Image: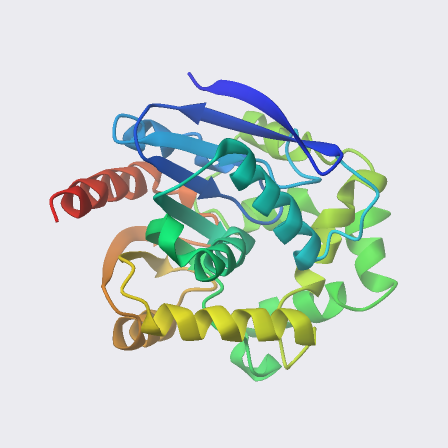
Length: 285
């Protein structure tokens, strides 16, 4: 039901799906997903704008160049993609690392952003490992350890963390779609680098500074914002909901019901209908 396109970007290629016409709505997935994450949300939004969902570089059907896949690499590829489509007056819909990419792009292009809808997002740096639930703490500490992380993700993960953070059973066919970009250790390098970019306890310092910078911009910008909360969630807990409600101007919060980290696979209709309603109210202003 979507157009599938490839676009040349910085000597590689990026795959995206698109549907609809009007002001662009840019959907940014995170780790270890792809535009497939948005397949059941986009149809709710498609009559309201030009819906665009790229696969980040090295992920989905996008090219797999020989790069570090650090956050800064992804920034460059996504900047070129957005400029390749000539996107202006952009509504962002973002998740996980897609939210960091989206917030960072919005702060740097404040006149080109119309609104930001975000879920299970990286709003703030994580000052200590003590803030983490013990489960995620041990996992992230293990992935961020040289040798161990390579064993866990490369020379051996997606089959466990994806169904682990969806409440309802993930089908084999959905799992096949998420496995498909990542058959080989070589192909899984972005999946390992992403957790090693997480701004935790001051490291890495360059991503910590990026997240600090866009958190300050979010708290000062009048851009309309929509935050989705799932029970219990993972990154976005009630605690983070309260911090956003207190500190981020022009924010609406929507509770979508039960869900974990990949809430698009638990409540896609709730998320899509809320975005569609939000775009209409923003147009009415």
